[PDB]
Length: 245
Length: 10
Image (cartoon, rainbow over all chains, first blue to last red; front, side):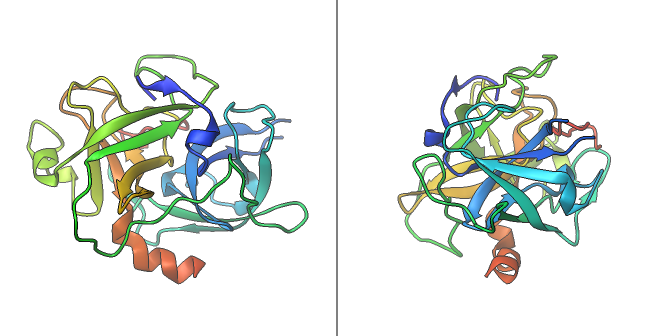
């Protein structure tokens, strides 16, 4: 995360940390969100270069990447589902969403705690407005030109950007479609970055934190006129219900 | 990897 502050999972207790196994400790690879006790949502691009469920391990309840955290829970991936129309197109990703069924060494799904909670999915519809300020979180880089990653969780606040604005040529032109969500900082100083992908974009809808987007792409980090782009979760609700329901 | 990726593996 560029900008924002360092924080503890207790402030993003749906955050899921997805690592890849090694031939020998596992490598942090990207973020995700606990959308139900057995199911983590993330980005499909996180799994392409090796799409085998046995190669991944999911930790819930972590403030510090790649070390033990009190109240941590470690899960194997029972089932790995990538969207059927996932696709890379030279600038960006499309239909960039994945579902992971998680399970412990002893069979259990996620056990709630102050550091492990689920996050709500957006409603089909809702009347009554809400704010366009939404939260991001992850272990991504703190600046686009860093080598090296922070090792401790960070969080920040960005504003949603209208499709129309995001589609202006100065922004991302016709690469942006109705299945995507754009979010940036109005003064271009806080953003998600490399290593934040798959992680959540938390808006506050009908009074509760809501998973409105998944970190998918953007040119650099906190660059002027280059918002972060998120899978628009509300668009995939029926797809999500048909798999986890 | 598409150019505007924010993936650690790109």
